[PDB]
Image 1 (cartoon, helix red, strand yellow):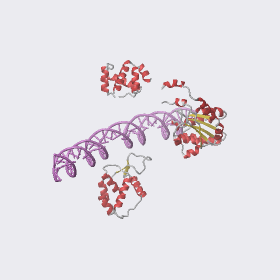
Image 2 (tube, chains in turn purple, orange, blue, yellow; image 1 turned 60 degrees about the vertical axis):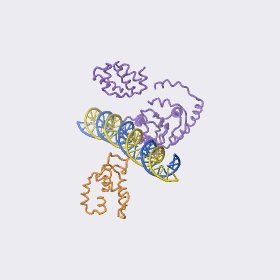
Image 3 (cartoon, chains in turn orange, purple, yellow, cyan; image 1 turned 135 degrees about the vertical axis):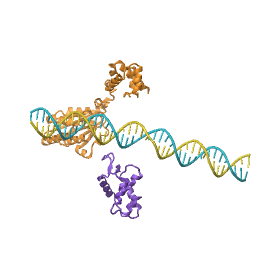
Image 4 (cartoon, chains in turn blue, purple, cyan, green; image 1 turned 90 degrees about the horizontal axis):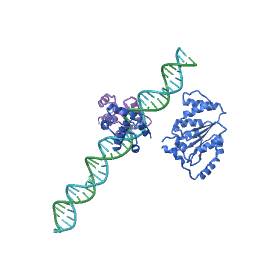
Length: 273
Length: 104
DNA sequence: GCATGCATGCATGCTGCATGCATGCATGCGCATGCATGC
DNA sequence: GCATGCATGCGCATGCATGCATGCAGCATGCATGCATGC
């Protein structure tokens, strides 16, 4: 999958229609801002990567106000991290919190006491694996229930409507907009995690390399019993005592290398290489 | 209910059971008899079963809740046939019909 | 001599029974962390 | 103000329960074949 890094040389097709499509999409920003500012939260749904449109909207209209961007497609994001970021910067508070619910209570009380605070949220790929928790969406909806917070979200998964319940629907107060941009999902697939054997075996002792080669050969022929494997290793004179063979087996185990959990085709290609 | 449970344990050798089978065979017993005064509905029998389980004469297997209701739950009896017979012999006012059903 | 009807043995299709293996789920344990308290 | 010890929350491994399939053997049934028997 390393070849992916070199695959970016392919040129796009029919880019003129995409240009007109983006120009048509650009004109809805004022209406979206008006709908946000009256107490509505907006979801964007449609085919194609819509990150570019959101970034354009931010850099065009949100350069004069406080705004927080969370690109949830990163698999390391959690709601507690968002809460900590809000507390540390929006309110500039450093004190730790005993529980998530207590942090939510503090934030709600602070925002209710201070009516001069306005915050904008820009969430990318709200359907992330880490944000699908019921408590996560409950927390986000409770946050969005305030009249001093504006929410723009994006949907890219098919089963998104199952996330929201009737009470959650009432809390979120959603409006929908269809914006299909046809953009490739380069960045959003970049962080996602869908050679090693050669590098490991390069610096290992040649006896271990031969033993592993024999093990691969037997595995491709048809798991070995310990006794038969020891006898065959004896026959090749790569082992002088069973303690040494078990030491080599433990060395292989330490690298997570009896069955080898490696695909047959990869082993066949590696043997000749 | 206990006599019905004993009959279930005899017919199905050492197997669990639920509320529905016991209710069905109790209904069979009260329907075979012409007009005996045992016309009871589901909720009262359910409450009686709950009380029996509360007294810890019946214990669940592989306890779980939510996934399985009180109904359709695998129950087992914690008594022996000779104990039931001896206790029934000393029952003060056991009716004839229930005694003969127990013997059958 | 032969055709027809009847009786029977066999092939086969259906179905009921016996069973192990993969996987999901609950649980117990054990470790990391934040808080109450004491000095 | 600090250290410490305790209560709590979460991750991980494990054992067990559940679903799911397939091959075999027995049985019933319908058909092919042999036998009797008259005209």
